[PDB]
Amino acid sequence: KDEVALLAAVTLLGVLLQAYFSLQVISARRAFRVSPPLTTGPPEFERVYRAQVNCSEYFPLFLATLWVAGIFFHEGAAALCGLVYLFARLRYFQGYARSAQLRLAPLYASARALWLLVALAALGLLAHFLPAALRAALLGRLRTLL
Amino acid sequence: KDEVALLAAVTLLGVLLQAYFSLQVISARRAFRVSPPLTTGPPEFERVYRAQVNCSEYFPLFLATLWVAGIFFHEGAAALCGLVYLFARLRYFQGYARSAQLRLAPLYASARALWLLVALAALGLLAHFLPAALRAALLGRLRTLL
Amino acid sequence: KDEVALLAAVTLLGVLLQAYFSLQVISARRAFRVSPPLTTGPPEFERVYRAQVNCSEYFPLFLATLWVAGIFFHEGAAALCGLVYLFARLRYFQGYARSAQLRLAPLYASARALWLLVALAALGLLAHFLPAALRAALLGRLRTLL
Ligand SMILES: CCCCCCCCCCCCO[C@@H]1O[C@H](CO)[C@@H](O[C@H]2O[C@H](CO)[C@@H](O)[C@H](O)[C@H]2O)[C@H](O)[C@H]1O
Ligand SMILES: CCCCCCCCCCCCO[C@@H]1O[C@H](CO)[C@@H](O[C@H]2O[C@H](CO)[C@@H](O)[C@H](O)[C@H]2O)[C@H](O)[C@H]1O
Ligand SMILES: CCCCCCCCCCCCO[C@@H]1O[C@H](CO)[C@@H](O[C@H]2O[C@H](CO)[C@@H](O)[C@H](O)[C@H]2O)[C@H](O)[C@H]1O
Ligand SMILES: CCCCCCCCCCCCO[C@@H]1O[C@H](CO)[C@@H](O[C@H]2O[C@H](CO)[C@@H](O)[C@H](O)[C@H]2O)[C@H](O)[C@H]1O
Ligand SMILES: N[C@@H](CCC(=O)N[C@@H](CS)C(=O)NCC(=O)O)C(=O)O
Ligand SMILES: N[C@@H](CCC(=O)N[C@@H](CS)C(=O)NCC(=O)O)C(=O)O
Ligand SMILES: N[C@@H](CCC(=O)N[C@@H](CS)C(=O)NCC(=O)O)C(=O)O
Image (cartoon, rainbow over all chains, first blue to last red):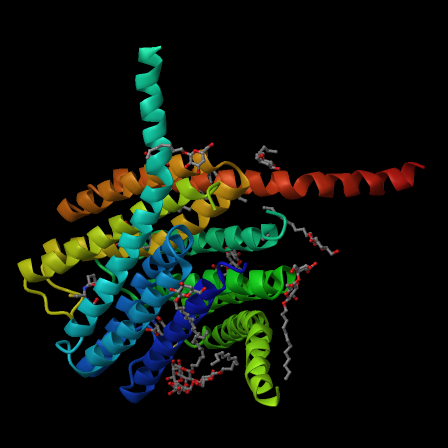
């Protein structure tokens, strides 16, 4: 609970960001008069909608990776990346909402942040498994010698 | 294990609920003959589909908050909120499926439950970080006095 | 911290798999020239898109279940199901990409693996709660007897 509080903070922040995104769709729904069963309408609504939707489907990836990296590599490092990602995503949502062009730059930023997290989580897992593995590997070569 | 079992239960219940929503869409797909690559068709299907999709995208928000709140504030209180949310969501799904008007009321219900969870997670996190911060704050203004 | 390392590993693998599906959509987006605000186009694109979207919405269900089962029943068993599921999903994505028919077989495979995990998680939670409940139940029926 001590070594997880930073993670949980970034997590809650992320949830708030997602809640913001979905509030913006609800607003763009009134603004551009697009009725609830409808997913489609004026391009400015559609861009806002699609941004929220792209952000929503990546969220679980962010969460999973945040925690895995935070626990197996470094809480502080993971939390910082999470922050960078979350911020990049806000920029993505806003760029996309303007033009389908202005989402590209922030998307790449967020992709890097997320890849970094994946990289950390990967090392942290290797650091965990590789020693135990190499030990069991060498034990195989020692049983032969004796 | 003992301090998270109630959370895990509500989590599993939520998973089941989502599984239900999913099965309903598969049903309404046969019922209204809407073939797999198509996301669109009769209003009856689209409402069912969109309800599941709305429920699906909030689910990680619910999970994230449920656990952060459960762990940092109170397992029982979080778990009870989760239950309230999950029920409200079931109502939302069924209301929406009838008319895009009948989803509104339960949506608000679910939004409240989810916001409360966010609030609890927020308090719990403040309670964790605040004293240690006030300690360091006093240490500063105490450097002055001494 | 390490009675969860296998879980964390299957989790990260899952994230990578989703990262893969997302990249595949990005690719099919250029390949069939479908501009970003648009969700719709040639059936070849739509199938790839829909696959990624179906995979993405079940992902949180997978994660939630994987961890709850892994923690309350057995880490190795959960992780193995996770692996089966993940692989089944890869096959789903690929089949769906070719034809909306070739998705069905792997979908069922994935559905089994996922239900199995739900089953394990359910038992594990029963094993935790059910002793105490049946005991209180017998006590009640025993208070009557004596
Ligand atoms: C942290 C969790 C919170 C996540 C965010 C979810 C918050 C939920 C709050 C619900 C607010 C929605 O508010 C509601 O929106 C719907 C569409 O979206 C509007 O639309 C509604 O009224 C219009 C009238 O113009 C009808 O034509 C339409 O069929 C009906 O759906 C309502 O006028 C508005 O009252
Ligand atoms: C510990 C609790 C376990 C909960 C696990 C969660 C799994 C979810 C399963 C709950 C199913 C909900 O139960 C649902 O009730 C409604 C009643 O309005 C029924 O509603 C049905 O009949 C009515 C007519 O009476 C129709 O208007 C409606 O279109 C139709 O769906 C559904 O047939 C049933 O599926
Ligand atoms: C910094 C601390 C973070 C923890 C916050 C915990 C909040 C718990 C209290 C729950 C009440 C929140 O209630 C919610 O408030 C926000 C205010 O931004 C409203 O949101 C409204 O303002 C924002 C401006 O930022 C608009 O983008 C949005 O379109 C609009 O609807 C929601 O319509 C309302 O439902
Ligand atoms: C302006 C008015 C604002 C009002 C705000 C009110 C503050 C709300 C904060 C409540 C959250 C406190 O979070 C509290 O954390 C402690 C951690 O020590 C938990 O305590 C738990 O773990 C500790 C170990 O440290 C055990 O000793 C204890 O048996 C157990 O219950 C409490 O279950 C939880 O209630
Ligand atoms: N769901 C995404 C998968 C790939 C992706 O994240 N694409 C990025 C870069 S093209 C995007 O901005 N998607 C636009 C959107 O989803 O609306 C999609 O359909 O495009
Ligand atoms: N994805 C949602 C984001 C905002 C939201 O959650 N909207 C609520 C209130 S308008 C809703 O019931 N959406 C209808 C739907 O998603 O089909 C949407 O497109 O509407
Ligand atoms: N979101 C799903 C919910 C139900 C589901 O998972 N359907 C399966 C079996 S029909 C599927 O492969 N859906 C195709 C898709 O989502 O593109 C849908 O709309 O179909």
